[PDB]
Length: 222
Length: 215
Image (cartoon, rainbow over all chains, first blue to last red; front, side):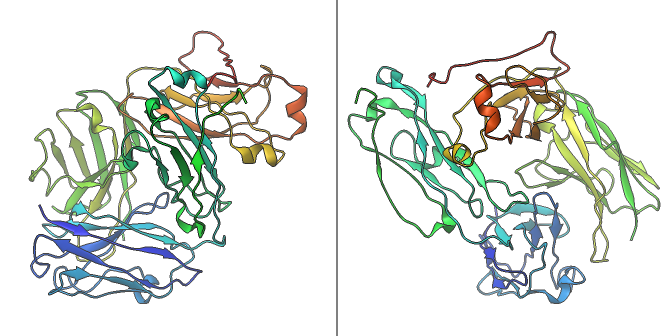
């Protein structure tokens, strides 16, 4: 089946500018046409149209001059450029594969937009573990604490159990405050304590801090 | 443009429930009306061409109809995952495209009370002077499981916030996220803290306690 690759993250003051990229794969885009979509949580769902198949270009009335499209058929790459994002232009965006060209069929990876009065901030590392029963219990759930930070992306990694994709971590949800909060809970075998040194940290995306430390058991006897 | 509506805005169903929903507009849009489905965290799906034109990749359980000012949709088979919200939308050369209000179609099993779980609170909640009590609320349906916080099992006017989550067919139930803000003074006078739920599936008053030393 035909697939694409999307891209994009926008974090600017009101009136934001950026250029994007979205390239289909498996077939030349000369024959097939495809328009970007708005997938705003809370706000809802909006879309775009294309030229030479449906014709011209679909923007909102004020958005008409504030968003622009082009196309690179030989490269089979589609790009999106904005110059002045609106105050409520704060949303994630995908693109929707078209077969009959007025109905969406297949999506890519996404593109997010952020215009917030808050500035870059980073949380701390507060991992959690159950009590001393793990010495005999083969498996148990762990914990972590992350809250009150700047845009959702937080990545939690553990050096035991399944791969890095097994950590129960997702982007958070924004409210009027501007901060963000989530949690991390992971269940890994406890027999690796005597063979692999445990390491936990927060891989916060807009953090601008890189500190790595190891993890040791509770050691309540000390 | 034009206005548009659906009947109803939310319906409850069950496995195999042949759901019958309607979309009405004032002036008929001829053959180019397309209903749409929406799964949370998932891409929507174009559903029907014309009135009942079936396309590739979809099981034949669907049946769309309606004419003139009214259009309908009746789906012969309901596999349990068919829980979704559904949009209606026309097609025209007019670049603006209008979508009618959705119908939050539900799959109803019974009236079930929530479960109880707890994790220790984060360190920022202690430092800020706003003491907090955590109690993970899960596995309830229907949604209206009214949540109250009875400090020392004492009923109060408020002190409760809610942000309910979605169906997870792994358990066929809802779940809830809450927020509690209180002054530091109230923490010292009271000893043991717990949360209460008022749901229509309860046969007796319910209160829960647990050990901080547990894990």
